[PDB]
View 1 (tube, rainbow, N blue to C red):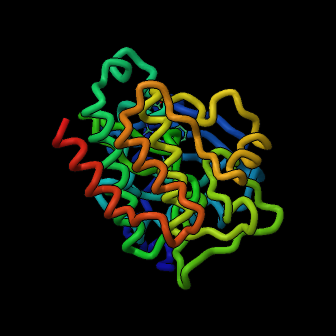
View 2 (cartoon, protein in one colour; view 1 turned 135 degrees about the vertical axis):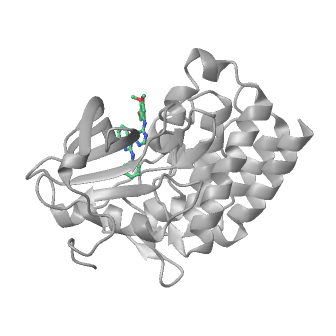
Length: 272
Ligand SMILES: COc1cc(Nc2ncnc(-n3c(Nc4ccccc4)nc4ccccc43)n2)cc(OC)c1OC
């Protein structure tokens, strides 16, 4: 990697003004702020000792390789402690949160499908660049002031050199959003993301409801093994439900590509 004095992303910390905190956690905080006074940005600060600085910055390095309108763009980094990762700011927050606001609640199925396609479009890019996300869920999709969506949180994202990535035996993941093969064997592929996308679609149409209503994780796994899939969400268009089912097919290879998903959702949108 280019040393910081030559890296185009490194910026003097003096260029940043942290204004409002958007999140506080075990490993640090995320603030809304301004770059050189006029440009609104999001600033991720690492909590010293909470985790490795190399681990922290690794997400930024990957984002240098994955630039696209549909993905939250890396803005800059401050690699001298305290460490910051600065990114493009999304005014309407996370999708899971937005869909619960007065504005979000009033969205038509037409606009929900539009957003769904925007998300598949972003994943199609990730798909084509030989990467995987692994944390695809409504909570990790950000919404702009113009109601456009972008993929966020690349913490678990990985460049796939061969067909898959194998996680650590101890690695744990959200059971309801993760593909069977991934939960069982720790094997992740772009097809695992496709399964997650299916779950995300249920989050979209139910305006942020937790998937598999009234079911615990063990119940979800048991039902899946029987061949059952999530029950049709209330008011979920059947065509969308059947698209979801494609994402949840038993064999990873039988699941569709994200480009296919994008194409279909775009047809669903232009039809409504
Ligand atoms: C979710 O909640 C919100 C988010 C945002 N806006 C925003 N815009 C860009 N990035 C992040 N943002 C990022 N960006 C991020 C970090 C690393 C890689 C890729 C993207 N990581 C985050 C972790 C925790 C909270 C915000 C984050 N947040 C604005 C909100 O209200 C006005 C809001 O509701 C409070």
